[PDB]
Image (tube, rainbow over all chains, first blue to last red; front, side, top):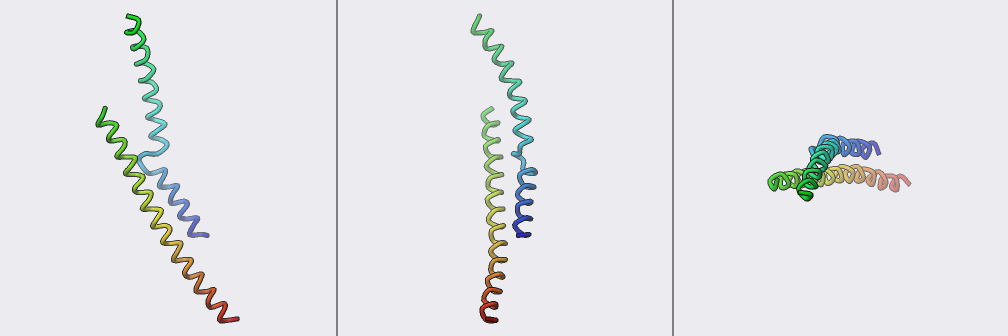
Length: 49
Length: 48
C-alpha cells in the first residue's frame, strides 16, 4: 500500500510536470478566447459591410 | 497554424506515451511486491 501511495503521488507529479497540463490549457483557453472574440467582432463587421 | 495544431497533437501524444510507460513500470513494481507476499503465504502454510 505504501508503494501504491508513492506511485499515485508519482502520477500526480507527472500530471503537474508534463507539458500538456492544466496550466497549459488554462492559458490556451484564455488566449484563444480573447482572439476568438476579437476575431468575431471583425467578422461581424465584414459581414455587415 | 497547421504546424501549430500538428505540434500540439504531437505534444499531447508524447505525454500520453510517457504516461503509458510510467503506468506499466508501476505495475511491475506492485507485482514484485505481490510475489513477496505470496511467498510469505506459502511459508505460512508450511508453518501450519
